[PDB]
Image (cartoon, rainbow, N blue to C red):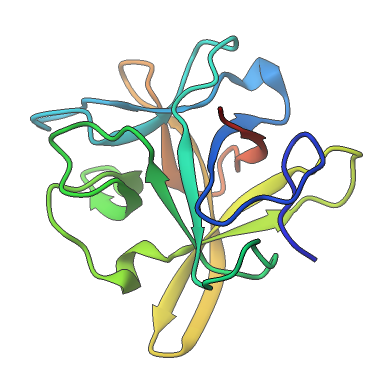
Length: 175
């Protein structure tokens, strides 16, 4: 069983998608914001605008195949990343508030990038996924945490590792 997009078509490996909430009242798509003493927008957030599709995100499987098997590790890359980032890849990095999804000004190894999995949320006609964060040690993988939303002091809806508001997403093909 492969990953399926919001329109019912298989997700294409390396293709670009908007990551939208299943419940549109939860906000819009995925984007970036500058927080703390960041020099540029490195914090990955969900748009507070329910009409916004956010940024196109490239979803790249650990496997060199046309589609994405459901248990595949994936990397999430901004199609149009902020110019200050060293690469387009969003990863989990420690923040002063705890592990959070961010872009980086450092080039990261594959073991820090291929760290996500989409987990199908049991039924609904439209394919809805939670976003797992996976530990890696050599060949071993443990996906025991989720990505969810933490609203900061300034009202940014940050993507963080947490059990608070676990994301449930639909994947809409960008064009």
